Amino acid sequence: GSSGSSGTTAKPQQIQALMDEVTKQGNIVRELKAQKADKNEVAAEVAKLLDLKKQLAVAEGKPPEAPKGKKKKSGPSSG
């Protein structure tokens, strides 16, 4: 197998990787329901998706579903 390092990490870099995930995910979830996938199997991806949207938007700068949804509040960082 591969040992040592798996590339380098960056702010503007990881983003490019996420974007792809947001797309692929959305699809994976669509097919899951289209094939009557197990409620458990689907849920798994579901949650992940909701996270991707954030890890993507936030990274860029936009707030995570700030305006969308009531429960999800801006909740800024303090430190």
Image: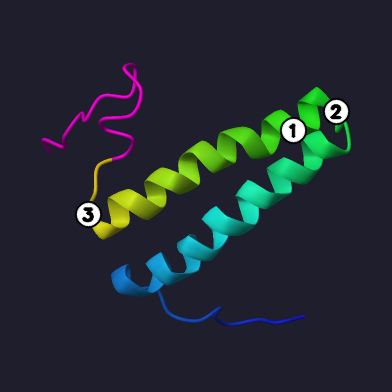
14 w.r.t. 46: above or below: below
Q: Where residue 5 appears, x then y in whole percent?
A: 54, 81
The part of the chain drawn in magenta is 64-79
Q: 5 and 14: which one is in front?
A: 14
Q: Name the residue under label 2.
A: 38
* Residue at 33% over, 35% down: 65
Q: Where residue 51 appears, x then y in whole percent?
A: 47, 41
Few, some or many residues within 10 Å of mark 3 (<14, 14–19, 20+): few
Disc 3/disc 2 C-alpha distance (Å): 35 Å
The image's mark for residue 30 is none
Instruction: Answer left or right for 36 relative to 23.
Output: right
* Residue at 70% over, 82% down: 2
Asked if the residue under mark 3 is in contact with the one under mark 1, i.e. CB atoms within 8 Å, the reply is: no
Asked if the residue under mark 2 is in contact with the one under mark 3, i.e. CB atoms within 8 Å, the reply is: no
Of all residues, the one furthest to the front in this rendering is: 34
Q: Quadrant of residue 64?
A: top left
Instruction: Label 2, secondary structure: give it.
Output: loop
